[PDB]
Amino acid sequence: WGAQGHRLVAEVADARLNPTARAEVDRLLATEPDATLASIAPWADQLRAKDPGLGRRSAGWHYVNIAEDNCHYEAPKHCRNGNCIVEALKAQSTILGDRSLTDGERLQALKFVVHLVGDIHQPMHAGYAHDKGGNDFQLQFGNRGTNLHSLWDSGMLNTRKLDDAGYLPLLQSQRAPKLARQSNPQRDPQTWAEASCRISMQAGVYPATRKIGDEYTERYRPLAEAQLRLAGENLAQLLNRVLGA
Ligand SMILES: [Zn+2]
Ligand SMILES: [Zn+2]
Ligand SMILES: [Zn+2]
Image 1 (cartoon, protein in one colour):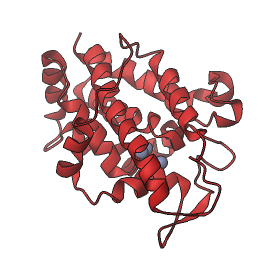
Image 2 (cartoon, protein in one colour):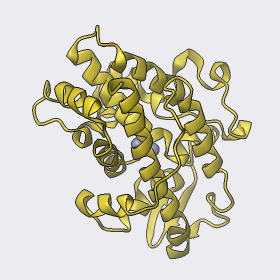
Image 3 (spheres, rainbow, N blue to C red):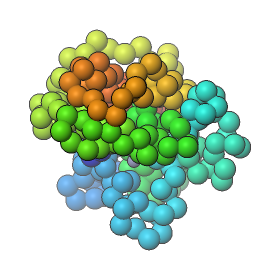
């Protein structure tokens, strides 16, 4: 997602934390002046942008391209050296839960968990390796040149013309998604990546033309918005497992 998608995932999650995970999240956030679950949600993208070390080391952690293998994940093939979102989210979930670590270490792991639960629910972050998750599929959206990756990260969300305070209750108005009956932080990432991959491969998500507009938005923006709600609810369920147990 773009920044707004990441914030909205965190805002949906923040309201669903159990009292224990509430207190532990607040304790870790207070070690960074003015940090909220929403405000840190885009951080992993700004790091990858600007940081010559962790930014370069974590750039592959935002995605996993499994569409050519029909959305069947294999860690050795699709996540060499743990360099994809499935293994990165598993490892950062373990680090975040490790109460023997410093507040600094666990807050950084929280920033990755908040961001990556967002990104693992963005269909184009689990798509084709060969076109870089739709980045190479250039297309005209209304009168504006963009690409299929950007369309799903922010282009369709931007058409609502809502700030976070307007967009949040819209997402909360949806019927509740069915989650796993129990969080398994080591197994659920593969499930989520595969599900996001299957959406990238659904009929029409890759359009038959390179000029699209209102028809595409009206069909697929509701799916993007369902994915933000699902991501937010899965993030709360994970944080309640890792920090609220
Ligand atoms: Zn993102
Ligand atoms: Zn993206
Ligand atoms: Zn990202």
